[PDB]
Image (spheres, coloured by chain):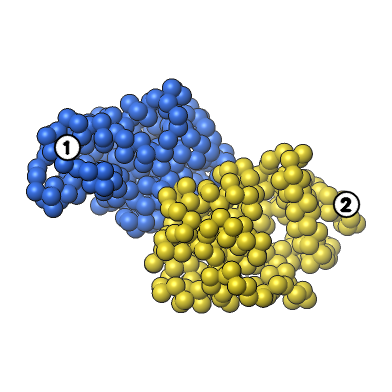
Chain colours: A yellow, B blue
Amino acid sequence: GLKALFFDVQGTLVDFYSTITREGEAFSAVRGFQADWTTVTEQWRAEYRSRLDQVIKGERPWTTTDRIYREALDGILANHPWGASLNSADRDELNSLWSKLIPWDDTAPGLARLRSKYITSTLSNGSMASVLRISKLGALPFDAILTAELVRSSKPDPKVYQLALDSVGIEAHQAMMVACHKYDLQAAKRLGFKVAFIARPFEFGPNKKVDTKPEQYFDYYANSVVELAGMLGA
Amino acid sequence: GLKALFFDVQGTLVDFYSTITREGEAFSAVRGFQADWTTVTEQWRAEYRSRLDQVIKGERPWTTTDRIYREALDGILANHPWGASLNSADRDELNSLWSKLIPWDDTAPGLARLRSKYITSTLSNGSMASVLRISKLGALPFDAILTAELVRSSKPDPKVYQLALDSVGIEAHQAMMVACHKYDLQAAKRLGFKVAFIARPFEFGPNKKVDTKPEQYFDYYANSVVELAGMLGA
């Protein structure tokens, strides 16, 4: 990280857990039902992985992640009674959430600092649509917005890390990946990137354990974007 | 136009003529010679687009616009008596100016104001790296940077404007094209965009004339970005 930092978004920068469980509470109660939004979040994400692997395994073909979440919702709604009462336009509204995820309280100030010293960009699996709307809404400054949609792929596919470099015009040794997911940081480190870990102990909500162990290949390890800004001289 | 705005960059938002003629005027000073930076500019932009046209046709493998300008520089430099004295690091410098184009005075505040009411992004023909770099340099605020290198093409190719709708999630009638070039707005309007024309009479410097007539098919017609912000109520 001597010229540009690339920031994973979901979990790393934004709280999808709180977003689905709180906004979904406004959705449920207003339709007269109560839903287990903690379970729904899980089945939706897991149903998004498996529906992504198949997208990465090569049999099921590429679609924007906004379309992946929306088809995943039809699968998991079928394992809830109330899912049947939601029409197709109800589920569009429910799916819209992923373009609305909430920042962690350190994301905006640490993004602002770092960009005062660096080129900053997203490198996320979300849609460009969602990631653009997530940053505008949450006031997150970025010099640019890149997602895996632009290469029709998915991290940890090297096509995706190459796009970071190509779109900013730098060598790997000049870039650093910022993610709370260690798989992401290995693929980047395989490819020569510098890497920073932001520990996100509540990524998946209050009752779950996450993996926040340090690791030697980590160039930096931080509990917030602001702390990472401090170790990088911003 | 009611949800998102897209801006052409060269000519429309940044003063490339001043950039080359000023910064270019200092490049020779450091090295002890003189040139017509006006003449170089015209030849350079011209050879670039001719070579560009050989990649659109496919008769020439696709290269980045930065690579494309770097080769054009070699071709035009043959015609000037100070050319042989620029080694290839001298020319790499010279080529770095296309990522340093200076905003027009109005550009920064109008984009700051127009981003308060709409989603906004570049949609220019240059490279991502250049466009990202000019924006960060001129402190120009955008929710996202898009160029036609993201689809290995160039305006008025319809992909380029589709890619605008795809990334933001909006259809063409809620999107607006902004440019000082009429070929660009002609395409945006056939594809259902609203279109705003920005008149840039000094685009090519003092001793030239520029067609900046209004048109029936323009949705808006302004002499600055801050003027266009005023007309859109921002």
Give above or below for A31 relative to B134.
Answer: below
Give above or below for A227 relative to A158.
Answer: below
Mark 1 and mark 2 on one chain: no
Say if residue A85 shows up in the picture: no
* Residue that appears at 43% across and 53% down: A170
* Residue that appears at 48% across and 67% down: A111
* Residue that appears at 77% across and 39% down: A59
User: Residues under labels 1 and 2: Cα distance?
Assistant: 71 Å
Quarter of the image that includes the C terminus of chain A: bottom left
Which residue position holds label 1? B83
Q: Nearer the viewer, residue B34 or B203?
A: B34
What kind of residue is marked 2? Ala
Q: Residues within 10 Å of mark 1 (few under 14, many from 20)?
A: some
Which residue position holds label 2? A78
Q: Nearer the viewer, residue B129 or B183?
A: B129
Say which of marks 1 and 2 sits in front. Answer: 1
Q: Count every numbered label the image shows and give the total.
A: 2
* Residue that appears at 37% across and 29% down: B52
Which of the chains bears the disc numbered 1?
B
What label sits on residue A162 in the rendered view? none
Relative horizontal placement of residue B64, taking residue A83 as reference (left or right): left
